Image (cartoon, rainbow over all chains, first blue to last red; front, side, top):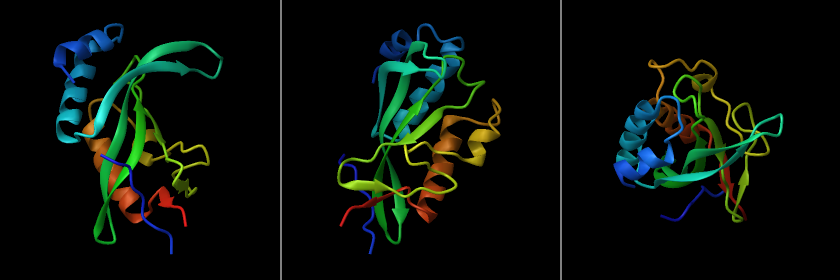
Length: 9
Length: 143
């Protein structure tokens, strides 16, 4: 699984 | 990933059998957490080979699920002492510091400060991280 993080707007 | 291979990895832990039971249940549920054997350095400078769990945990935030990367070190006296926990951002992320994460990615939670076997375990810890990171993500993606 690839690590993801939520975008900052 | 094998229950016997793990016994080997933690063969010099004080509570070998407890540590294996927790690790087996944790990695059976959170399939992206891999056990890894690496050196760990204490404040005095002494190193000990210790097991950690490293990989991602699925965290819902605003309707999507992210795979937040973490590393949890099980000290050799686990589970009498809490695990030492870090966010491990890739180069596409940055750490959002706060009451719970410092600039090095060290995580600080009341569940960790108040640790006490067996009211405290790895499953209950991960459950707490998902809720907390679900309100306040410790990593955001870079622009």
